[PDB]
Length: 405
Ligand SMILES: [K+]
Ligand code: NI
Image 1: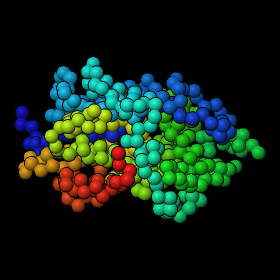
Image 2 (image 1 turned 45 degrees about the vertical axis):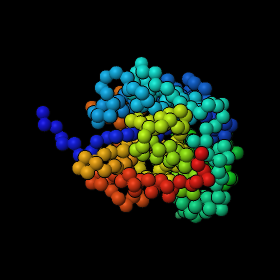
Image 3 (image 1 turned 120 degrees about the vertical axis):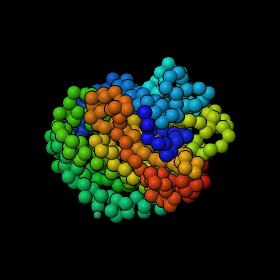
Image 4 (image 1 turned 60 degrees about the vertical axis):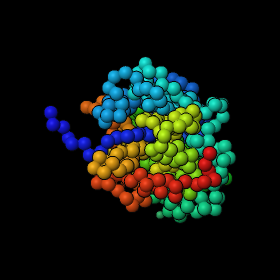
């Protein structure tokens, strides 16, 4: 019957995904000392993807197949052919397994290759060129930029967030902890900004809180019976706790003086996947451009891209602004009225309840989705997309040539 008159046609999609639910990457003495209670144990090694984590990613893969079929970009049946779908992952187990999980959902029994760099025992600079020394941060500029975004000092930062720290202390039962028996997390563990040529980090309570509140969220998404020892009982509490995780990434990963450098290889890969040109084999042996590119990375990659491109978002129903399986989705659309080219960016994610309930996703039960705007874009169409030329200029301005591969 008479369907909606197509105004735009989808040409290409690039999905930059955080890996799915993983076991905590550390088990430190300080984590033991800040609570009298025992941390729940995990079914996989430190930092590895859990089976449930993979099942949640495959749900997003299944959903993406349904909606890309609806958009006309992929075929309803059969496998995608001749590199129509490509997958690139970081070398870590949790990212490679995320790529395998997404392929399993998008195109089951089609053994789509999960590409990595040749040496999987060494870091891939695409996901952080600082880590292999491709380039370095500017120490004075990064320090000033982060401290300013903190409110002028890390003390000012923690001074404005005492409500959230007190909520974490309650969940920890911190007053009955060994650290307390000697009480306030921020004063017991003074936080300072450490800036080196290759990394930025915060010490003390700020970084501890970001980690621990992430762990509670992973416990919830994993389906563990009582996250935070049963002391997290409503959504306001979840939002208050994860604000500490979000706040650290705002400072350390969204600040442009860090984000532009760390995101430059990803920016280049995204722009080459989205740019119309004769298809040509390039990075990882992958032929670009193509229909669908899935990149399996990390929390910091989403934040770095958001900071470098001036994309801002909060995720309704998902307290972690960079959640497991969260996807930054870049799409190239052709406007049929004049066959002009446009870029849309959105953030696709499972709500915390969808993770808690292990909700299979479909057109009828979609993940959450936030439409984004490139703040620097001066040429937008009626749907808020940026012109291909405008997007290209933004990326060329944001990228840092010394950080490119
Ligand atoms: K302030
Ligand atoms: Ni996150």
